[PDB]
Every structure is written in structure tokens, then in C-alpha cells.
């Protein structure tokens, strides 16, 4: 029954360590992809990634960071930013039963799980493993490592759904507020970047391997010669809040979440059916009586995936399709963190009135003909935006956000 | 607004491969803990575990099982049982937008995450890794691997929260129905059992190590000489359904879910605060006009944990406490699968009118004095039952289930 808005955001990504840096990159169509000596040394074929350009050493208290893996660290930093951006003080959100946290990652921590196994097999056994691997490697690490130090008393758990992970976290947060159980819920996620995890993707042939010499051109959603996505890492968090509660404290409102769709393909384990995406987008548009001005597609730069989504978009919008752009062309695929980060990019476009470009399209794919895929930064007042997130196992999520009247 | 009931269940645990075996074990007070050569050979101090005594070979189609890890296998078999028990046919739950699945695991698959890293570092590299490690190792493996083959079209994702994982999955399923978004939601989870995961717990001193010579006595919740929990694996699944929809199809109803609590401690990373549990139980009891007849405790058999929960119980019920028993004394701690399996044990006690015994208590802990702890199988007509699930990161979940009027 309650209305839900976003009143704060935080982000650590391949194209910026805060929203100011991210805004700059989006407007310039700047790539965050670099060559990775780590991936190459591991024996992989894909040697490019969207890495976080930031030394996190000493940014978090020793007694707090000892339980964390990179996914949790990225999410933590993003939350600190979100709290400051939202203008919330400790006395308001801490030890408050009406304030919760829903954040997750797609793979937990392959790095620390492998570390533990490797240590256990050495001559020092248990002594070499140490007592902190469980909180670093458990699937709920991102929520557990944040809810505790931030003194959260409300809901506390992680939602995981591969590449749709953080989108579902935001959606579930919305639901908690609509149910009247929470007034504020920090929602987002994080994902570490390491060969331990990346090699499994390369092994299934999902990663780009043809552009290692020109890193910034590897991620090329919609380009006729795309050859897989570029793995990335990072984190993001947004403050989901009940409308009256936000207005009562004089919060800055970025937008209202007016639609949330969550569906399942029930078809293929790794490829989207398209049919599920159609139902997801429609579900998210139910009751939304303003046109979608911009759509931030899932578009990972894969042969099948890119066009399956475009086909879904055509069926949903008919001859009234919105401006479209795939920011992954610039940032790479941050997996579990993709949902929240892309929701954030969309919010920035909505807040500053511009559409970020879909870069690296040298030869548009035949199946993309006729659609308005923006390839250059465009100034334009936007009112309603949509963001898609699809994951392995046929899990779909769509979020629709709209400016609040006045 | 909608009322929610459980119309089917499935389970694969250390004390039974279906509800018939589980029921017999609960009544007899039979342990499912055995000696593990695998754990001993790995270099661990804890050599006992609650293993699934079932050969799963050929129980799942080749093309489907190739994408799964053990957690998914256990959950899959549990879902098959639940579907048959619920009396649902393919046309009833398949390709139906109103039917979903919410199931998870606490750690995904440490075994396959390590396999991938090991294979990659060998002479075959990517070829040895293979194309199936991602779906086996990703945190959402359990939901992805079930939703796809069972043709699920509704919600599809995993909730993870350490030892409260599958309890939150059931609670979220309840919310989806209350929101009127789904008519049926399969909820539960699974967890693999392997040294790759167990050694990290031993490394932090969380597992029992003093009773390897007498495996069946290692797990002893509330006993003065307990020394940590006994790790276990397995799966569970329940059919969460809207009341009218269930009645309309002549379904057998085990009970109605009349309360669901989800809170956070915001205190310690590994130990429960007690305060969070109090708030969680009170939240789940709100509006419930009948007394709690039986409480299936979290009780993992750890020095600190066991008494913190007892203190919370005492705070909530005072001198009028319900009958209490920790089934983990029999089954071991199945981590991510604990929530749903224990909900199932509780439903069986409600359905068959008996209280399972809290075994292995040779010297009751002094802090348990004055509480109604049951140590002998006791026939008694139950009407309302409660089950607690707490996890690392201070995450709490409580479910309250009650019989439906006549
Ligand atoms: C998006 O759907 C692509 C798949 C993301 C899965 C989450 C990350 C899993 C890492 C597992 C490492 C072996
Ligand atoms: C319950 O809270 C006890 C902790 C369970 C955490 C989930 C299982 C994580 C295993 C993988 C990391 C070692």
C-alpha cells in the first residue's frame, strides 16, 4: 500500500569509486576495462576485466574487516557512501527494528574458499586456515558483514540469483516496505574479482577472448562481432525508504520505484528464453501509466543473450520502444553487483537528464535494426526509466523508477 | 491479507530419506551421526558428521544432474517428494506464472569451487574445469537447478543467511502469497557435506572434537559437557500455498503459517546476542491467540549458543515456557538446510501428536533449570508450534505453525 523511494546511493565500480566519478565516466563513455596479468597467468583465454581502481587497505576498521572478503568490502564502502548521501545519522538507523538490510553476491568468495582448501592441505592444516574463512566465504557474507557493524536490527539476509542478484535485493526491499514491516532497507550487493571465479566462466566459453590486445573494445554489446562478456567486480548500495518517512525527514528523493518484476524462464540453464523477460517487463510496467523514456538493458555482449533481450523488448513495446543503451559495454559484467550498479547508473541519468551511450558498436547486429540504441551521450529530460537483470537458471528481474512529482 | 498453509513436504536428512523414515527416527530418538573417514583423512579434529545415507546415483536424469552440486541434488529429491505429497500434477505447477520457488544453501558448493581451482591449475587447464562448474558453485545453485527442470515460471531466487537460510526462504514464500503475487511457492534448501567446507568450521573451533569414539553422543544440546556442533548435510522442501487455492483443490493441509519473524542482532559476527532472538520470537507471535505448545530450538550444542537461546526463551515465556527439544542432538547441524528440515520435523510432531526427545543430556546445564525441556518421546496433542533458526552475522528467523480449524 505504501509508496517506496530511493533516498541515497553508494557505489564502487570499474568506472568510478563514488557517484561523481561514475557520473563523469557515463557522460564521457569512458571504459573501465583493463588488461589483467592475473587472468593471463592463471592460464585463461580471457585477459581483460572491469577492475575496481582503489586500494581498500585501511579503509575499514581492523576488527571489522577481518571477517570480510572483497565482495563485502565493496558493499561496505558503498553503504558508507549511501548513508552519507541519504543524510542519515546513527541515532536514526542504528538499533532500529524498522531498518533492515538485504544485500548479496553471486558467488560468495571463491578466493577464500580455495584459500581454505589449499591451506588445509598443506603441512600446517587447521592452523594455516585460520578462524575467519567461514564469514568470508559463506553465501550470506555480504549481508552478515554489513548488518553487524552497522548495528542493523531489522531484516538481515542475502538474496542470490546469479546476474540478477542485487536487482532482486532491491525488489525484495521494496516489498518489505509495502508490507509495512520496514521504513528503510539498505539494498545492494558486491562481487569479488579473481581468477578463481573467472576461470569457470572462461571454461564454459562465456568470456570475451578476441580482444585482449585492445581491452577497452572487448565489451561491445550489440556489435556484430561481440564474443562474450568481460567479467568485472565491485559493489553498490541504495537506500530504499517509505515515502512519508522520507518526506518527514526532508530527504532528497532520487526517484520512486513504481514497478518491480520477478519471473522465471523454466527453460535453459544458461541462456535466456526471452519469454520470461517479456512477462517480467510487463509485470514491472503494470499500473505505470507514463511511457518508459530509457531502458538500461541487461546486454552483456554475448551472441545469443543480447538479441534475445532485444526480441523481448520489441514484443513488449511494439512500435513504441524506448531509448536503449547497455552500460556493460563501458563497465563490464559485475555479476551479483550488476543489478544495483545499473540501477544506480539509471538513477544518475534520471537525476542529471542524460542518456549514457552504448559504446563500441562498429557494426550493429542485424537484429538490432530499427531500435533506438543511443551511441552518443544525449541530454534529455527523462521521467521514467527501466533496468533489466537476467541470470543463469532463467531468473529475471526488472525495476522501473520514476521521478517524483515536483 | 491472504492466509498461508503448507500442503506438502519432502526431506532427505541424516535421520531419514523421506518423511516415513524421519518420523520413525524422531519417535525412537535415533541419532544420524556417524564416524567420517573423509573428515579424519583431511586432517580435521572433528571426525563425526550427519551424512545422508542414500546412493543418489541415477535418481536424477543425466542431462539435469550434470548442472548440479549435492545441495541441489538433495533439494531436488526433496521437491519431488513434496510434489507427490502435495498431490500436484505437472499441469498444475509447471509453466504457471502463479507458481514459484525460493530455496537456498548456506555455502553454495565449496567442493566444486575447489575442484574448479584445482583443475585449472593442472595440466589440462580449462578442459579439466569443464562447462558445468558455474551452476554447481554459484550461490543460487539450489534455486536455479530446480526452477529450470521443474518448469517454474513465477518467482525464482535463493535467500541465504547462514544457519537461518531455509527458514527465511519459507518466510519469504509466505510474504509472496500474502502479497497476492503467487498461489504456490516451493520453499526450502539444501547443503552439501564435505571436508572442503567442514574444515573451515573446525579451524574456528566450532565443531565437536571430544567424542569421535562415540559419534552418536557428540551432538548433545543443553548437556553440561557439549563442545560444539556436529556438521551435517541434506535437504528439505515444503509446498507453501494460499488457503483458498489449497482448499479448492482438495489438498491435505498440515498447518497454517500464522507467524514469521526476521530480525538482526547488530552485535557479534559469530555469537548470538539473545536480544535479537527475543525480538524475533515476539514478532512471530504477534496476533497469535493460542499458546505455543512446542518449540523446536536452534540449539546447536555449543557452549555459548545453547544458553543464549535459553535465556531469550525465558525472557519471552518466563515461567510458562513451552515443551522444548533440540532435534540437532539427533540430526546434527545441516546449516542452510536446518531451517526447512526442522520446520518439517515440527510439522510431523504436530501432525502425529508427539514431542521428539532432546537426547544425549546426561547432565543438564544449570542455565536450563526451570524450563520445560523434554528428554523422552512424549505423546501429546499439539496445536501450535514454533521453530527458531539463528545464523552467523546475527540473523534471526522464527516460524510459528498452527493446525487449521478442524
Ligand atoms: C549471470 O547470470 C551470470 C552468472 C553469475 C553467477 C554468479 C557468480 C558465480 C561464481 C561461481 C564461481 C565458480
Ligand atoms: C550457522 O549460522 C552456521 C554457519 C553456516 C554458514 C553457512 C555455510 C558456509 C559454508 C561455506 C564457508 C566455509
Image: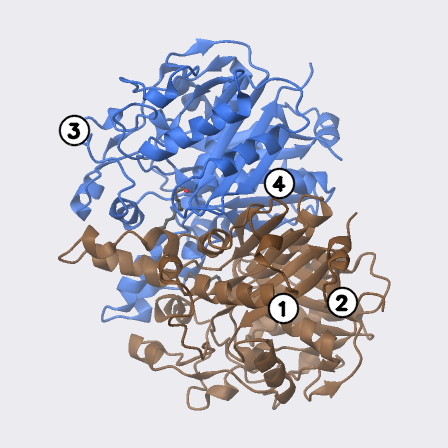
Chain colours: A blue, B brown
Q: Kindly identify which residue carries mark 2.
A: B315
Q: Is residue B377 visible?
A: yes
Q: Position of residue B229 (x, y in %)?
A: 51, 75
Q: Tell me the element at label 3.
A: loop
Locate residue A305 relative to residue B371 in the image: left or right.
left
Q: Are marks 4 and 2 on the same chain?
A: no
What distance separates the C-alpha of mark 1 from that of mark 4? 33 Å
Q: Are marks 2 and 1 on the same chain?
A: yes
What distance separates the C-alpha of mark 3 from that of mark 2? 65 Å
Q: Nearer the viewer, residue B223 or B105?
A: B105
Q: Nearer the viewer, mark 1 or mark 3?
A: 1
Q: Chain letter of disc 2? A: B
Q: Kindly identify which residue carries mark 4.
A: A173
Q: Nearer the viewer, residue B214 or B76?
A: B76
Q: Position of residue B273 (x, y in %)?
A: 62, 61
Query: Which numbered dot is residue B85?
Result: 1
Q: Kindly identify which residue carries mark 3.
A: A213
Q: Tell me the element at label 2.
A: helix
Amino acid at each position: 500500500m505504501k509508496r517506496v523511494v530511493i533516498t541515497g546511493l553508494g557505489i564502487v565500480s570499474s568506472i568510478g569509486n563514488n557517484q561523481q566519478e561514475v557520473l563523469a565516466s557515463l557522460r564521457e563513455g569512458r571504459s573501465g576495462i583493463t588488461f589483467s596479468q592475473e587472468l593471463k597467468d592463471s592460464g585463461m583465454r580471457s585477459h581483460v576485466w572491469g577492475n575496481v581502481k582503489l586500494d581498500t587497505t585501511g579503509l575499514i576498521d581492523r576488527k571489522v574487516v577481518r571477517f570480510m572478503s572483497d565482495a563485502s568490502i565493496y558493499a561496505f564502502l558503498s553503504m558508507e557512501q549511501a548513508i552519507a548521501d541519504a543524510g542519515l545519522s546513527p541515532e536514526a538507523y542504528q538499533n532500529n527494528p524498522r531498518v533492515g538490510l538485504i544485500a548479496g553476491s553471486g558467488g560468495g568468495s571463491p578466493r577464500f574458499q580455495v584459500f581454505g582448501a589449499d591451506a588445509m592441505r598443506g603441512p600446517r592444516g587447521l592452523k594455516a586456515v585460520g578462524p575467519y574463512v567461514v564469514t568470508k566465504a559463506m553465501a550470506s557474507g555480504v549481508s552478515a558483514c554489513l548488518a553487524t557493524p552497522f548495528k542493523i536490527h531489522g531484516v538481515n539476509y542475502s538474496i542470490s540469483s546469479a546476474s540478477a542478484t542485487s536487482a532482486h535485493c532491491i525488489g525484495n526491499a521494496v516489498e518489505q516496505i509495502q508490507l509495512g514491516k520496514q521504513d528503510i532497507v539498505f539494498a545492494g550487493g558486491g562481487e569479488e574479482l579473481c581468477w578463481e571465479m573467472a576461470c569457470e566462466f572462461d571454461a564454459m566459453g562465456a568470456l570475451s577472448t578476441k580482444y585482449n590486445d585492445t581491452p577497452e573494445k572487448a565489451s561491445r554489446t550489440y556489435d556484430a562481432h561481440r564474443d562474450g562478456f568481460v567479467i568485472a567486480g565491485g559493489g553498490g548500495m541504495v537506500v530504499v525508504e517509505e515515502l512519508e518517512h522520507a518526506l518527514a525527514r526532508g530527504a532528497h528523493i532520487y526517484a520512486e520505484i513504481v514497478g518491480y518484476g520477478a519471473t522465471s524462464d523454466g527453460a535453459d540453464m544458461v541462456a535466456p528464453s526471452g519469454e520470461g523477460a517479456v512477462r517480467c517487463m510487463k509485470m514491472a510496467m503494470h499500473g505505470v501509466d507514463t511511457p518508459i523514456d530509457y531502458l538500461n538493458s541487461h546486454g552483456t555482449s554475448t551472441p545469443v543473450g543480447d538479441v534475445k533481450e532485444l526480441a523481448a523488448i520489441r514484443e513488449v513495446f511494439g512500435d513504441k520502444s524506448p531509448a536503449i543503451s547497455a552500460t556493460k559495454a563501458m563497465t563490464g559484467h559485475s555479476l551479483g553487483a550488476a543489478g544495483v550498479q545499473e540501477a544506480i547508473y539509471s538513477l544518475l541519468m534520471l537525476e542529471h537528464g542524460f542518456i549514457a551511450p552504448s559504446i563500441n558498436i562498429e557494426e550493429l547486429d542485424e537484429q538490432a535494426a530499427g531500435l533506438n540504441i543511443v551511441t552518443e551521450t544525449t541530454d534529455r529530460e527523462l521521467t521514467t526509466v527501466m533496468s533489466n537483470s537476467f541470470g543463469f537458471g532463467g531468473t529475471n528481474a526488472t525495476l522501473v523508477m520514476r521521478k517524483l512529482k515536483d
